[PDB]
Amino acid sequence: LAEALHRAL
């Protein structure tokens, strides 16, 4: 999830 959020942002 941390990574998914990095990408999203």
Image (cartoon, grey):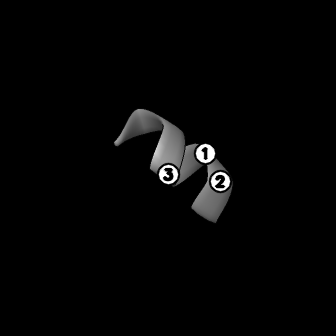
Helix, strand or loop at disc 3?
helix
Identity, as a three-letter code, of the amino acid under mark 2: Arg
Residue 9 sits above or below residue 2 on the image: below
Q: Is the residue under label 3 in contact with that under label 2 (CB below 8 Å)?
A: yes
Q: Which residue is mark 1?
A: 6
Amino acid type at circle 1 is His
Q: Are marks 3 and 1 in contact (CB under 8 Å)?
A: yes
Q: Secondary structure at mark 2?
A: helix
x 49%, y 51%: residue: 5
Mark 2 highlights which residue? 7
Q: Is residue 1 left or right of residue 6?
A: left
Which residue lies most toward the top here? Answer: 2
Residue under pointer 3:
5
- Marks counted in the figure total 3
User: In this view of the protein, can residue 3 be seen by the observer?
Assistant: yes
> How far apart, in angstroms, are the residues tagged by discs 2 and 3?
5 Å
Q: Quadrant of the N terminus?
A: top left
Q: Residue at x 65, y 53 (%)?
A: 7
Q: Quadrant of the C terminus?
A: bottom right
Kind of element beneath mark 1: helix
Q: Residues within 10 Å of mark 3 (few under 14, many from 20)?
A: few
Q: Amino acid at mark 3?
A: Leu
Position of residue 4 measured from the top left corner of the image (x, y, whole percent): 48, 50
Query: Outermost residue toward the left?
Result: 1
